Figure: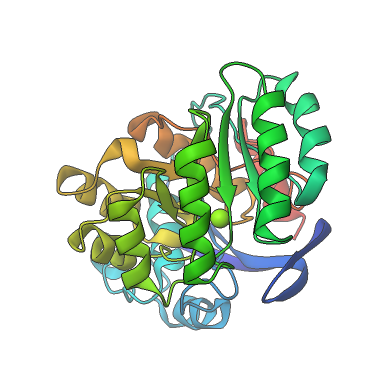
Length: 320
Ligand SMILES: [Mg+2]
């Protein structure tokens, strides 16, 4: 079938700041496939700067190197080193003549700002049906955040679930003290601590997960299928935060699941991708059927309403 690709550079609804810099926009590639009868398919390739080794420029080069027509064999030549590209082409191909997709509103995790702000930001989300939250930690001193956490756990309604995200900012000693605190004062409301240590300290990450009672989730540590596989083979007992748009061919996750990966240990999250990628992911969720709130409560930075009509895709494409 014939295909086309177009780059996109979209300003974020509002700036997002991390320890690796500040970004005011998200860029990527949109793929449009069309068969001999006029049926169309769409896909999105959007690697996230800093996450993994794949770069948008490498994806663009791939797109310029591929033949004017697509086939399963041709797409099989896409380098394993370009997981977002594998995702984009795979989802694009599968969507040909299948849009729009049947999807559903899975529970979404609500984010809570660092500091005391967490105590005033959960109410609105809870009143909108969100029962899982993720609070950013490792910003203030451990003592200060622990005091806030005690108050937060006491204030949250029965049934609330809370995730703590350290964004790999704690050093080994601080992480150890935190888990000791959680082991004691932690409420059955703590779902897990996300990335307590930076990815380079994998031995410490594994050791902590194998010894502390509070569950640990890998995020920054797991971008591609290759990294997830590596952690599965290392015997990771915790959770895996899967960013499907950056992962690779969706079939690779299904293969891992048929093997040593536990479905209950997965949390599907956003890589600040567009509506095409997000809708493709929700389509995939009809099969994987998540059992934890999705880390897609990122509307503040990038809103991407699910696409419910084929014309909606066409409009997005033509607007470029
Ligand atoms: Mg995280």
